[PDB]
Image (cartoon, grey):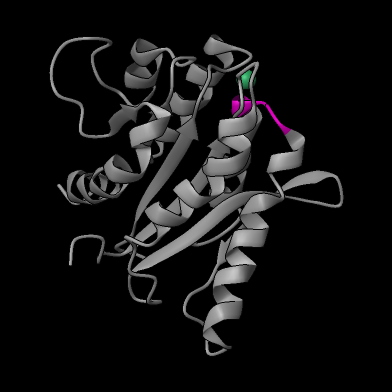
Amino acid sequence: EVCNDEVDLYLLMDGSGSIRRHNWVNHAVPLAMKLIQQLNLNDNAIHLYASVFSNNAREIIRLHSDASKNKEKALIIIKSLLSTNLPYGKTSLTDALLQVRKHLNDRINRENANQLVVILTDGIPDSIQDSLKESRKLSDRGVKIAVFGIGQGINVAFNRFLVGCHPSDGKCNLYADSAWENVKNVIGPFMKAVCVEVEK
Ligand SMILES: [Cl-]
C-alpha cells in the first residue's frame, strides 16, 4: 500500500567493482527481484524500466507484471532480462544515467507521475565527476535518484551525495546500504521508504 503511486522507476544495476565477483553474480538479480516485489505494477501506478543488455549493447526496457500472459513466464522474463547484465560486469554509471535522461527526453510522461532512478551498486563509478554531472542534469529535470549500496567496496559519502544528501550528516531516505549477508532483509524496507519520500 506504499509503492502505489504514479511513478516511472528506472532500475539500474551497477556492479561488480569487486575482485571476488561471486556475491554480485549470485545475488544481485535475486536482490533486484526482492525490490521489484515491493512495487505495484498496475498501469495506473508504477511503470518499471530496467537497463539491460541486448545484442552486445546496453538498452532501456519496460518490465511488465503480471501481464495477461502466464504468471511464471512474466517472472522468468523479468529475471532473464535482468540477468543479461551479469556477463558484462562493471559498466559506466555515467553512460547509464545519460541513457535514462535520453529515455525521458524521447517520450511524454504521465502528467502526475514522478520520475525515479534506483541504483543498486557494490562499487564506485569510473568517473565520480562525470557521474555527479549526469545526476544533476537529471535532478534539474526533477528526477529523483535513490541508491542501494552493498558490501565494502562502496563509498557511502559518494552514494549520499549522488542522491542529494549531505555526504555524512543527517538522515538520507533515498540511501541505504548493507553487507551481503543482510541485504535481503533491508532492501524491501528501503524501496518502501523511497516511495514515501518520492511522494513528498
Ligand atoms: Cl562512470
Percent position (x, y) of residue 18?
60, 19
Task: Check residue 191 for magenta coloring.
Answer: no
Where 80 falls versus 157 (above or below)?
below
The residue at the point 28 percent across, 44 percent down is 185
Task: Check residue 93 for magenta coloring.
Answer: yes
Residue 94 occupies which quadrant of the picture?
top right
Q: Nearer the viewer, residue 74 or 135?
A: 74
Where 157 falls versus 171 (above or below)?
above
Q: Tell me the chief SS of the magenta region.
A: loop
Q: Which residues are magenta?
A: 89-94
- Ligand 1: give its quadrant: top right
Percent position (x, y) of residue 52?
67, 49
Where 82 falls versus 6 (above or below)?
above
Q: Is residue 118 visible?
A: yes
Specify the quadrant that holds the N terminus: bottom left
Percent position (x, y) of residue 145?
38, 36
Q: Nearer the viewer, residue 137 or 40?
A: 40
Residue 186 occupies which quadrant of the picture?
top left
Q: Total label count? A: 0
The residue at the point 36 percent across, 37 percent down is 183
Q: Is residue 42 left or right of 166 when viewed as pictured?
A: right
The residue at the point 42 percent across, 31 percent down is 180
Q: Nearer the viewer, residue 28 or 100?
A: 28
Q: Is residue 136 left or right of 144 when viewed as pictured?
A: right
Percent position (x, y) of residue 101?
55, 41
Where 149 falls versus 59 (above or below)?
above
The residue at the point 34 percent across, 28 percent down is 178
